[PDB]
Length: 211
Length: 145
Image 1 (cartoon, rainbow over the protein chains, first blue to last red):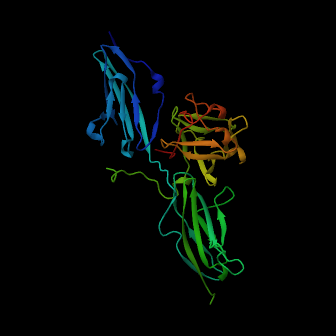
Image 2: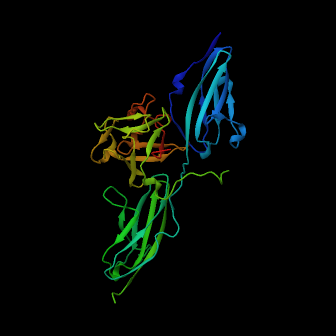
Image 3: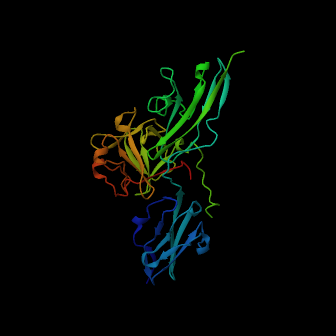
């Protein structure tokens, strides 16, 4: 006859459980005691009801565990296991963090870069806003000429990378042009790529005479 | 519902400082000032805030915002903090099946040497890692919950 005790604290030294949303989370609190103690789980210090999350949750007395499948952001919080018998009660609280992960090519915000107009001698900027889980690589490209032509015999347009992401580059998301000339007018493209794929959107620079 | 669930993720989120949380023991990757690398469960630790950036498509630098040191792996497969960026600081960032990230040394990609953290919080050695350990699974987290 004895009050509850832990049988395996090693599996309880993790102070933070961070998991990808949609994955399954499992919490355990191996316990002992005589009579055999009973287990109950609390969420944020209060009774954890099956209706508190869609799809509810499952417990396994054989393993003193709580299982939640397809976790969603709202599952974040503190999960307390309470083990007890007539001689006493003990508990342990785990904290759960949920993060949305995405394996997708970069997504650009609609409307950016936005068109711009300035006079000869003026300055302008183009902005690109990106959503990307995998680290994105940004490059600004202009559609240029060669031998007077804007396209090659293979139909490919002549392109020139004005700048791109890197430790030697400041502010990759913004292309700033200074003391512009009518020769600067044209299409400026923001092409963003991660190992999964790419996306691109462009804008037009209009350059008016100084007059 | 899925429509009610809220969770930040604004444009440019990829450039904000992150913590590289290892699910193995639940440690945050840490780059100490003296150049050593290990893990810690102290989310308030000032040497776990990292700035990730793609130097080349799918190739990233992992830099300590606190000391400016770059994470790197030597020819022995050991992690260390480098004051200056070099070829040993580049890692191939990829998302695995269970949606955790793995980071493989670009320099030693052919050998599949990953960045990893053992349950005791100490850095794993490149040669001792492989596609299946929990030690190589990472989750980039916001600095604060």
